[PDB]
Length: 252
Length: 67
Image (tube, rainbow over all chains, first blue to last red; front, side, top):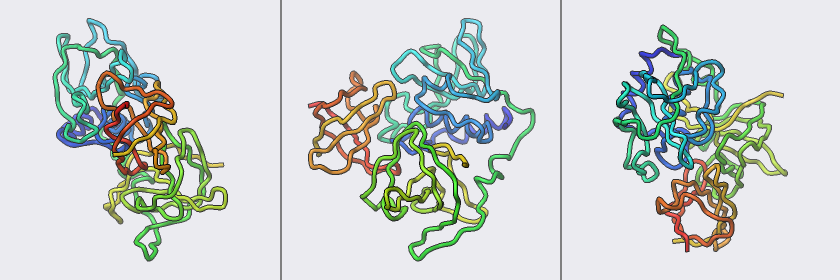
């Protein structure tokens, strides 16, 4: 768990940038909140679903969901959730009082899909928020996510096509959004494949770094497939970094 | 550019798939891709026009219009 200070530095570092780590359709409102909550919980909470679904995720004791009331005082690092629309809206709170609060948010204006609207600081005079998610921040700064097994390079082979690969035997279950699996190679230029559906699962035997993505390699119906499972920053060694996952990994 | 039919659309989740008229791969459609703020839902079997964007997650529909 990171500190409230680290929350503030994360929010300001992401102002004016586009967060699309869930990999789907530009800079959507829930992409920012998913990325924020994943960061401040040191990877323990990967929020699934639409913005209004945030309040029903399992925060594993690392956050408390509060209802907005005329007396509620939001704090830096709260996650504001609007639940009274079809899909909701979500924001990272910077400060607030009883009259208004300020926040970092994506897609307030509807420009996230086409990409011109970045994460923006805005003031809201309680124009729809119904809930606030308050993290249980630690008192001291934490580097746990950046040094975790996930964000350390380790040992990889490279093939003649520039793909990094290694053996790893586990199971992957697809998260909220579907992902297109590619036939034969972990390449976005491969047009053949099939849609891996949410909550679908496969055992896999290979992990690959290619085309800005981490992929799993597996066999289905006699064909070799590669499924992207999170973003990769394209770097190796001590500069290697990968994004929040697009599903859930398990062992059997 | 392309025409197709909505294969299914889960209004609760806000996404579904379109079957393109030319018989290519099904195309993912997210509610944020639907043109017009009054919609944000699509119906099974509905005729649509759209642009195809190739993303990390696969082929996706953009600028989806109900015809």
